[PDB]
Amino acid sequence: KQVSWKLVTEYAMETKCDDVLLLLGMYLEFQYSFEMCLKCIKKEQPSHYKYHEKHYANAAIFADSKNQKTICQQAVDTVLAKKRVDSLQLTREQMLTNRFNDLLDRMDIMFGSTGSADIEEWMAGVAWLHCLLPKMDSVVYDFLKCMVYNIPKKRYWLFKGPIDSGKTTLAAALLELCGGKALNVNLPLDRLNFELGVAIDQFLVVFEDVKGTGGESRDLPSGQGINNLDNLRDYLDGSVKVNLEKKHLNKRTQIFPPGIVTMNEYSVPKTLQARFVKQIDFRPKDYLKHCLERSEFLLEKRIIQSGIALLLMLIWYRPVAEFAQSIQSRIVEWKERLDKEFSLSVYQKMKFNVAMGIGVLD
Amino acid sequence: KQVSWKLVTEYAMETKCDDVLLLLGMYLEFQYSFEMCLKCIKKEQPSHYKYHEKHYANAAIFADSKNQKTICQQAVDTVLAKKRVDSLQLTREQMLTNRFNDLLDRMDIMFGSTGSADIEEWMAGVAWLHCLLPKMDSVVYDFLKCMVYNIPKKRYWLFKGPIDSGKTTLAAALLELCGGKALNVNLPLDRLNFELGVAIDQFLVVFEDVKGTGGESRDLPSGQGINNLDNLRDYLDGSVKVNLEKKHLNKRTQIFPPGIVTMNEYSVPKTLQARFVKQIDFRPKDYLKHCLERSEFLLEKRIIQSGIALLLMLIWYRPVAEFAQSIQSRIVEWKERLDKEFSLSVYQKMKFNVAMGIGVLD
Amino acid sequence: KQVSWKLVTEYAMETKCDDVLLLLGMYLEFQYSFEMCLKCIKKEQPSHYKYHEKHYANAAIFADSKNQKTICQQAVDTVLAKKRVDSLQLTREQMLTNRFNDLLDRMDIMFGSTGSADIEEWMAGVAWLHCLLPKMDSVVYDFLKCMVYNIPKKRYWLFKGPIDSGKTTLAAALLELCGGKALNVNLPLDRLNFELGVAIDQFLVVFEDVKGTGGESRDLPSGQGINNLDNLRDYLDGSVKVNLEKKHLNKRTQIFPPGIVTMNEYSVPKTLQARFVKQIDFRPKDYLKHCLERSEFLLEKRIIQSGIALLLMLIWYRPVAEFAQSIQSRIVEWKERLDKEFSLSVYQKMKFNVAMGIGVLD
Amino acid sequence: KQVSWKLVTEYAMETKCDDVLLLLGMYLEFQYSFEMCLKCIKKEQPSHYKYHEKHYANAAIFADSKNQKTICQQAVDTVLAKKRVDSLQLTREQMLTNRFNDLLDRMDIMFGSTGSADIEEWMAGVAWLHCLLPKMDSVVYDFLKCMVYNIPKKRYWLFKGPIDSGKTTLAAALLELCGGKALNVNLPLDRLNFELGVAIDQFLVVFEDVKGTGGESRDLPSGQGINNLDNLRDYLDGSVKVNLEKKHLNKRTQIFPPGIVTMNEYSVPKTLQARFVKQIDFRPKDYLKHCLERSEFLLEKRIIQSGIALLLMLIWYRPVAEFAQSIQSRIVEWKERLDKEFSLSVYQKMKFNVAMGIGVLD
Amino acid sequence: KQVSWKLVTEYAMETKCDDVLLLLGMYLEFQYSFEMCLKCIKKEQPSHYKYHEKHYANAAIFADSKNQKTICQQAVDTVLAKKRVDSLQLTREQMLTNRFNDLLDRMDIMFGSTGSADIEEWMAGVAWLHCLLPKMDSVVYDFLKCMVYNIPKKRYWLFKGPIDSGKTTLAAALLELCGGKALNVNLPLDRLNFELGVAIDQFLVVFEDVKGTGGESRDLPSGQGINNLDNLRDYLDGSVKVNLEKKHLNKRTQIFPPGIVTMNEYSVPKTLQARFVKQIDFRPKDYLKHCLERSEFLLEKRIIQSGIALLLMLIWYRPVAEFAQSIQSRIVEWKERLDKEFSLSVYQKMKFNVAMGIGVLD
Ligand SMILES: [Zn+2]
Ligand SMILES: [Zn+2]
Ligand SMILES: [Zn+2]
Ligand SMILES: [Zn+2]
Ligand SMILES: [Zn+2]
């Protein structure tokens, strides 16, 4: 009779779906009676089995509409219209809490009744990560406060180290823990601005492997990335706003996002150095490598690079009140979960096993 | 049933909202009953709580409308249309007063009971800023008269100074007080029109850190800024109109905007120098530097580079009749609030502190 | 009167038809009575005769409809939408089984009573192919497990060999058995992203004939392939996601696909070599060469490079349980047909022939 | 009342019209009573006088429609939708037969009651062509079987010869006899792919005048075309499919089409040579030139370059059963036509006249 | 109420109006009553006064129509559609007669009672032009026959001469008499296709001032024209079709148009020279030069370079039967008017004047 465009927009806003084709393809699965849906019975996809029921009726009418895409276009624009509002209205801590909430939804399913994730292998990831840097759980908390506070000339951390030292991994988990885009400044001074535009609306940015000049004697390729950063002081310390680009034309004007610079031991100009409020030197450690050699699951399952392993470390080490009021109920809920499955002496042993480089789970 | 396109346009026009996705996002939040509206109950957004009730009805119908996007378009074209009308019809002073009303709009909120802004700190900034130059409030006033009057060969100021000397800060605060855009002219003589086109319809312009080839011994980079500036004499003194490029074509033909040129102490050709009606030299001052070290909040909350700090200086030093008739009543309103809050002896101790380099609030 | 958009979409969805002009072309052939339909009477096209009757009615109305094109669009967006859904929700094994069902779909037709394919010849290809490498069926199986498992640093195979050595053939057959795209990386270090973007949503990738600067004496060209590969270590071992360029912008962010690298015997940097979990060397064999000279049909009917030849090898050598539960019944169906058609002693004489270099069917 | 979009699509599909403007302009000529049409009475254009009658009525209503182009747009898309189907469904021999049928329609009018063509001048063209190469009629048949069979590593012929030797002419008639696009590989390695995309959906391709390096001593310009061909082995012998481009993005992936390479006597690398299954050396012959000097009509009327002269040679020399069943009825029909107007001794004399270089028709 | 789209299309078709904005502009002038129409009363525009009355009614309704633009579109597509039809169906002579009718259309107006053209002056031009070359009217006639016949290797004329020698003038007059475009080939060998594409659907072409590298001593520039021409032998002699580029792609495939080549006395390669069926040499003549000095009106009113001057020469010298049957009656009409206006003895004195270099009207 008359397809309800509203319900479709609701489903989209509930699934957080900003892809028109992906929305179309999912709403259409609902057109079949749920009174038999195996996707639901078998709980295949949460984005499906939690809405099929409610939307059967409307999806059945939807499958007969003459402009299903136009409808999905408005549902999507709605998700984007909201993503644009929060962009200007939400505070940074709220930005961070939403990210956090989205990661918990991911964790709720991973370690749930209908999920594959093995939490024991993920706490092993926490043990390995907490052995990568001293007072690692305090570091992540600090980093998070640095990013949310986002204060001029104190918004960037510099990860320096050889390859396979750990900065890339920690810098990756940190990225996913907060949401944000990595960028590449090892480009020609004219190709730069396009890349810099990527950081639009982002919470944080990670300048992956910035290459410098000097050090070719130590087998390190000369690049202009370091040189470009020293020319992007305005961006890094962000005291005033900046104009960002995309679509071959100027878009947003804002405070460049705070972040991390991953580097490979190139000499740094004193003017560049001064832009980093914190520096972390990573050196490859033998036991850590050996631990992995005897714990393939941490790599093959991409656990130690996952921002989830870091959120997990927080929930496990950090005091509840350190989180936002709004999300604390969900945090205590996970602490109890965790505390109920792992004792301290068990988690501690995992850390001991890493130190001995033998296999977290031995 | 029958959504009102004019009611949405009203909302857009009173929010000065030129963003479609944003307008859409804002409006859809009014579909919910405002009775138990927390956003209103907590008064978290002026652009929301001030209009939710009046638009509840309309928004609720808008929610079930099939072309929400199209409705928002017309509302935005109406706002762009109004801005196109002011570009061609308001006097520069009417342009400056609207800008002032807008900043004031923020001040009511920042310093309101919902805002988080500390007015003592923003007055600490007036004091610090008032120690950056001799007779600073008169310096600001003149600039303003200069910009509004926009008179041939007497519309450009040259801020010359080392680094961390204040020119960047004052040029930034001035940029925000009047509206306008910063421009980079240290570019390829052909990738110039690109940037010069950003000046379209802008009130004033600021060429930041113009660099010259001449000079190098004193540690100053190359850049072609000075060079380029000398080839834009017609844009600078504005005796006749000019053709500005944007959208990768020739849009607006207008008198190029007045403004400032920030520079780092190079050799300025006589022909270029003759283009500036006034030139200010900034030399690093220890007390101002030490003072910041002890007055972190000035930089951390981006106060000294705010056009709001400067608007507070005019309201605090200058007489009412100096403002546009249309706004005075609002200024007087502020003077009183301010005079009720700070004694001249208090404000004076503040400048004394900056003078002794010890943080304004001691 | 009132054409059914859903009936056309059904037709499009069951033909996996993503082409609009093509869908339109197909559907308009159903407007004619199927009673005296020669295309059906002669069963010349599965995508036609299998659906003509069910769609006669609809097609006849479609013929007098004013927006046939628009109808076809939605039907295509529905198919693209389904493909967008599988990209994000199927496991790699479910991806491999669909691919297998499709190839099987062809096999039913090629070897059917309407097809022109000689099954003895395609079994001559299994034999020839089974003489190209030791334990070839186990080699194929592993690759498959490798690709499906897509595990960090253990997802790339290196096919190294001269020319006319078999690597090109096997890499082509393997490419068709799993789906995927061939890629050329011997390009300008900037005209690279272009090609790397072709890997988007693909199941596996094949970098064909990667060339290196090192080496030249032995008559091998220059090319920058090896060079480039070494700069794509992150795309190869797939520990973390990557941003792929297509449409002249940044589309999909995904784990780069697993695959093969075909190479012509250059010097492979240790850092690059460490990127391949397995390496196969192909050396020209006389009997295989002579055998082709006498087994023209193998090359002339493009059989040895077919993924169909290889699917026939798995069905012929491998046990049922090795296949996905969902498909086995169809394989068993084929095994029987095959076992009823060829005796092991016959197939063995075939390999003996390839061994003596005299054409498989003597 | 209501314009019949269907009839318009039928006319378009009957005229094989894929040009919207050309369709619009022709359907509109039908709006006038045919009961007086001089275009019909005078039989000016077959595309007009064979449909005016049937379409008057509908064209009269058409001339009053408010969106004649939208209608013509669907008629066209229909012709393209069909051209796309046959692209995937028709066999190569059917592809060739359709071409053949289209050439007969052209010949039916040329030598008909309302046509200008003089068949005697066209049989003179056949006599001249059959004197250009030994057993010429067997050559064309062979070439046609080579093209239809389209077998890997046996799909290309190489025409080598000085200028005005005859390869260009024969290669042109062959092109038109089969339908297909010529391409130019004498382009920069980066401009290549654009050109190569032209061969999409084509029956055959003709690489016109490929220039090499070496031979500048014999007054031959150095080019990179030969060099590019040796880099297009995959394309030439076509054992596996290839990706083709257009519209600045990737389109079809298919077996590159078979064809001819016209060359000017440059040395050929043994690796390139091996790609041509046949080579034909053309040497300018005196009597042939003299014959033309005394037979201007063969050139001024473009007869010896016309694919029609070749189809005519076939019908005249070849046995009916050598053609496809479907088209034989039409072939015997032309043989009788021909046999009724030209005796063997007459045609033979024409061949004798060419040999003597004096004028086919003397 | 209900505007007629066909009536507007009629207006567009009879004005040969291919401009949308222009058509719209013209039509809206008919909405006003034609009773007191001054434009009609004063007969200032044929494209106006000749149709105002018949369209008053329609135009008045058109004025209140909501989609005037869309109506005009169809009317223009109808005119473009007609032109697309003539491109493919008229004989070159029918093309030349339409062109002649059009120029004649102007002549009726220029020399009418509303026009400002002095016919004595335009006959002064025939005389001057008739002294520029021996047997000029026969020279014009031949060119015309040449162009219409468009016969292989006999379609290009070479106008070779110094400067101010007449070649430019005659080539311009000839260009206007037949229709066509001027082309610049002294360009980059890659920015050539651009210009060559302008020849699309044109009747004849004129390569103006082709320059050669050879030669320089005699004060002649460089340019690559001659060079390029020699690489376009296939475009020049038109034995086979060619692919022309426009819209930045490959549009029309056609026989390249016939025409003239204007040149300034360089060295023309034999291979290039063989491309011209006729070559005319222009050498500066004093009397012709002096004559202009005293016959300013010839240059000032752009008469000697007009195709109208030349059409007047054919009507004045040539016999009726030489024209197309379809137009003769109109020519005879003109001959009489002309013979009634000028005696042969008068016209002869005119040539005598040009001969003595003293202005034709003395
Ligand atoms: Zn379901
Ligand atoms: Zn509210
Ligand atoms: Zn059928
Ligand atoms: Zn007719
Ligand atoms: Zn009028």
Image (cartoon, coloured by chain):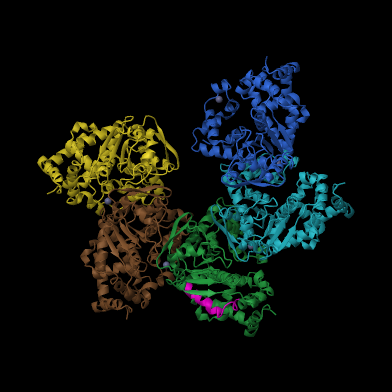
Chain colours: A brown, B yellow, C green, D cyan, E blue
- Horizontal side of residue E271 vs B186, given as left or right: right
Instruction: Name which residue lies at 17% across and 51% down.
Output: B294
Relative depth, front residue between D167 and C57: D167
Q: Residue furthest right?
A: D345
Q: Is residue E176 visible?
A: yes
Relative depth, front residue between E179 and A229: A229
Relative image position of residue A264 (x, y in whole percent): 35, 63
- Horizontal side of residue C59 vs B355, given as left or right: right
Q: Residue furthest top?
A: E362
Is A284 drawn above or below residue A68 in the view shown?
below
Instruction: Name which residue lies at 61% across and 60% down.
Output: D232
Relative image position of residue C225 (x, y in whole percent): 51, 63
Relative image position of residue D168 (x, y in whole percent): 72, 52
Task: Write down the region rendered in magenta.
Answer: C129-147
- Horizontal side of residue A124 vs C355, given as left or right: left
Q: Residue furthest bottom?
A: C345
Residue C133 belongs to the span the image colors magenta: yes
Q: Which quadrant of the picture is home to ligand 5?
A: top right
Instruction: Name which residue lies at 17% across and 47% down.
Output: B121
Is E49 drawn above or below residue B294 in the view shown?
above
Residue D352 belongs to the span the image colors magenta: no
Relative image position of residue D310 (x, y in whole percent): 77, 54
Relative depth, front residue between C301 and B183: B183
Q: Is residue A105 visible?
A: no
- Horizontal side of residue E59 vs E101, given as left or right: left
What is the total number of numbered labels drawn onto the structure image?
0
Image-quadrant location for residue E193: top right
Dominant secondary structure of the magenta stretch? helix
Relative depth, front residue between E47 and A218: A218
